[PDB]
Image 1 (cartoon, rainbow, N blue to C red):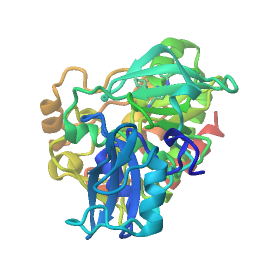
Image 2 (cartoon, rainbow, N blue to C red):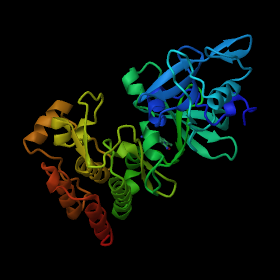
Image 3 (cartoon, protein in one colour):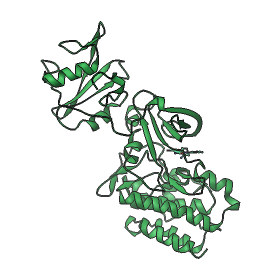
Image 4 (cartoon, helix red, strand yellow):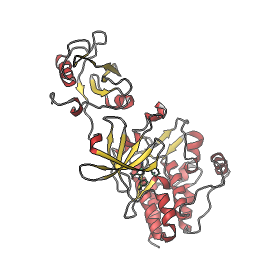
Length: 372
Ligand SMILES: Cc1cccc(Nc2nc(N[C@@H]3CCCC[C@@H]3N)c(C#N)cc2C(N)=O)c1
């Protein structure tokens, strides 16, 4: 192990950002080695007095050192520090205790080939791609380096969340390329693309039964998310994906948040908030919950049965908020069955406690589908 190159070491995390570092270092003396993207030097990061401390690993005459002996590799330096229990510096008194290994989700850049751009997200372009080992087709999310540091820190949230999930109606994470820049999130490629484009393109040919089965899929995904305490926050047709067999998967988990007691209090400072898909209490008071996702699901039902019409077309975001406060809601689409529209109206109850559960939504859509 100690003879293996640095890049192969389990405790070498490469281009991991500072915020993820604090996530991974749990106990006193927990440590990892990474590359400082800014400075272009190796860094030893160690938890001490509850906070991560960062030490620049010095290099001279092909020997690596801190303030003591030099070694011809960083793994030899780390082995020395761990085995001797010598403080990293006399001044700091920091002592290594446990190497934090990479999780199973870390993917080497060499394992991936990027293809054509397929979309544009809030953080940057999304590309198609392939895993070199087996020709698995993938979708690859990128993060533009010019984004504000506070927003870039949030990029890996989608991956942290999806690491935990497995469901037929939720997009599958494949890995995260954090060993070098540029940082990527790698997911299964859902080849039929987004649901909004699907509806608009294939509209005329779609049977009501098929539409009900697809939103039924969306409801199952959301039921699963609710069971995991996940609040999605960005549910919309454009953020659902369609497989070759017309199965719908929920996608785009960048804004999603896990909350054990079911409520996420927003910072208030979110840019490009999907106002027309968002519940009043979430906009007014920053109160996001499964109940605010239910509101969004109502809008998704509307998009589905209008075959991809744009909601509140004649209104600005602010006018839409004012309209909704007055009791304004979207009209019944002509292809929408009466029963679907009654469910839709319940999803848009002004008070969050009055909206249906995702279980109820799933079961109601299923019952309607068995008529058609
Ligand atoms: C053919 C085709 C066309 C378009 C997308 C995809 N696939 C994806 N698109 C995505 N984000 C997109 C951002 C822009 C609007 C559409 C998507 N929401 C995301 C995410 N996260 C994942 C995929 C995926 N895993 O296949 C595939």
